Structure formats: structure tokens, C-alpha cells
Image (cartoon, rainbow, N blue to C red; front, top):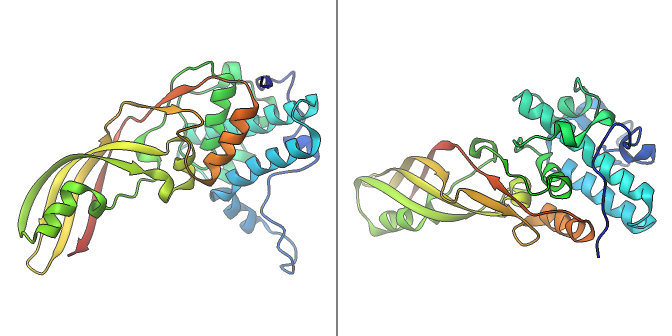
Length: 270
């Protein structure tokens, strides 16, 4: 039987991330000399930040115990920071993660889930932790993330209909309309954590030249309307951490929409 983490609130939040006993930063680099802002700015743009916050939670739970009230407070509060940063990224598309996380107009220690919680996640590196918050506290409400925000990289050669035309040795212009399974976790550790394997529809044009050069121009959208967030659908190193934390704490599974479309232009030779 699992433990309940309370939702972030001004009256329960700790005064800081990690109760001032740890913080989210770029790694100790021996012999580098003093740590500087440019290095920490980059650290926050990278997926490693997500990994690091999650690992820190696990390390804390290991050392101090999962049922210890302080532990549950730290969990609540830390996740609170992420929700707050991600809100700011949804609200201000294009700002850095460092800026959204540190210089938000609403103070992260003041975060209140019940009243501030968003249905739109940003798709940036803070999302996997936001997605966990919705499991803990969201009572099964639908969330969504726009397909243009998830870092899709499509290889047309791994799409059966396309591969076939290319391998067939034909030349000219060919219309494509197909559905495929796409493993986000194979290359994207962030999107892999909370979306994993998705189903996509694409429609477009394959152009093959006499010497085997091909170009695919097309549009990609989600084929399934929504995707489950549960222990089984996580993929990748971040996902595995979500699974371990999910198994320890009370919450509800819920579904994530993937509205939107992207336009792709990929190329190769046969």
C-alpha cells in the first residue's frame, strides 16, 4: 500500500527546493575551477536537468525513508518548482529553461497545484516531472501537449510504405498516406519518458531521382487521439525513474492529448 504526497500549496511548501539541503545544478567538474553561469544555463537547457532532479528525489528517499514527512514535503515542493517553470514556458514560448525556472513572476515556493495546475504541458525538459505531478495530484484529468513541441525526428526509411517505394527502384513523384508506430524513446529521452511509443499519421509526396536521391515532403499528425500515462508506457532512462517513483506513491493514471501537426522535409539516397 502506497504513500500519499500532498499537493503543492503556499501553506505546505518548503521555503526552497531540497529544503536547502540540496539544489538543482550543473555537476561538480573537478579541476574546472569555479562554476559559472553559462555552464549552468546550458545545464538547464539539457535533459540532464530532469534526470538530475529525479535522481535527487530517489537518492533522498533511499537515504531518509519514503514515509518520513520531510521526504514527502520535499517531493511535493521540488515537483512544485517544475510545474512552476513549465507553466512559465507554456505562457512565454521561446524563453530559456533557466529563465523560466529562476525568474518567473510567480515565486516557485508559492506554487499552488489546485489553483495553478495546467492542462497544457510545454514539451520541454521540465515536462516529465510535470507529468508525474499530474499523476500524483491531477485526479485523472486529461492533459495535452502539442505535437509541434515534442522534438519529433522522422526517418522516412523506417516507414514501411516509404521504404518500399524507395527500395522498389521507381523514379518520379509518389503520393504517400500511411500510419506508423514511432518510438520517441529511441532518440528523445524527454518525450520518451511520458509519451513513449506513439502512433502517427503522415500524408505527403515522395520524390525519387534517377540516381536514387529521394525527398519526402509531408505533414505528420497523431493517429491515436490520446496516450496513457502509466508505468507501462514510459520509455527510456527518465521513464524508468518515473516508474520507480510512480510505484511508491498514490495517484491516478490519466490521458494525454497530442493535437496539432508538423510539416516535415527529409532526404536520402537509395
